[PDB]
Amino acid sequence: KFQLTPVDVITAIKAQNAQVAAGQLGGTPPVKGQQLNASIIAQTRLTSTEEFGK
Amino acid sequence: ILLKVNQDGSRVLLRDVAKIELGGENYDIIAEFNGQPASGLGIKLATGANALD
Amino acid sequence: YPTIAPPAVTISASYPGADAKTVQDTVTQVIEQNMNGIDNLMYMSSNSDSTGT
Image (cartoon, rainbow over all chains, first blue to last red; front, side, top):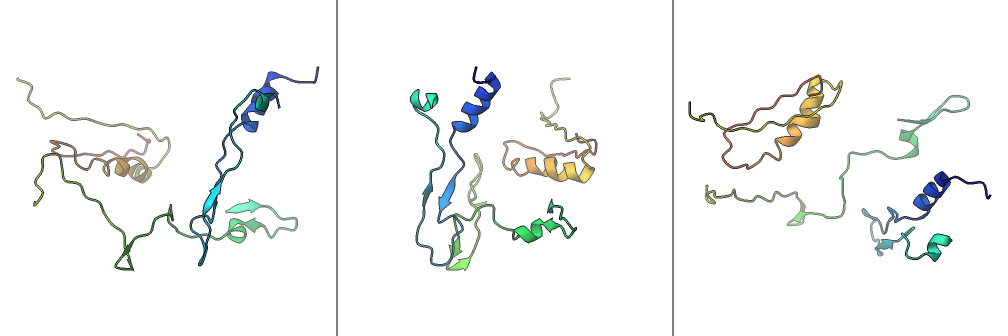
């Protein structure tokens, strides 16, 4: 109906659902005086069936 | 390293878009022997070898 | 004869078209840095071939 092959289901759930090679605030090597270091948590892997319906 | 061809022709090289240097593969840990820059070697003895030799 | 000759192990890898000195740096010298401290090793011998092997 809504004009689709499994292939778009594949690429969909793949690139939609994943962890991500994020990086860091205050990234190393920082600059003279830098006074924050903390973790970038970007796009995360899933958990539920909701997160999969959506 | 070429990144793109220009409309007139003065192309855009990586040279231009970013800075380039021979650099550490990792800048997390820094080694200061007596405050002076240093780099060390961690040597382990063989498997049934003499220490003092 | 009795089994007489000192036992030995060879490693072989393929890197097609790569020139001799390339295989000398891309495969041969990579191994000899981790052949540091094997037990009862008499000697070591490396072949860096320009057919990539």
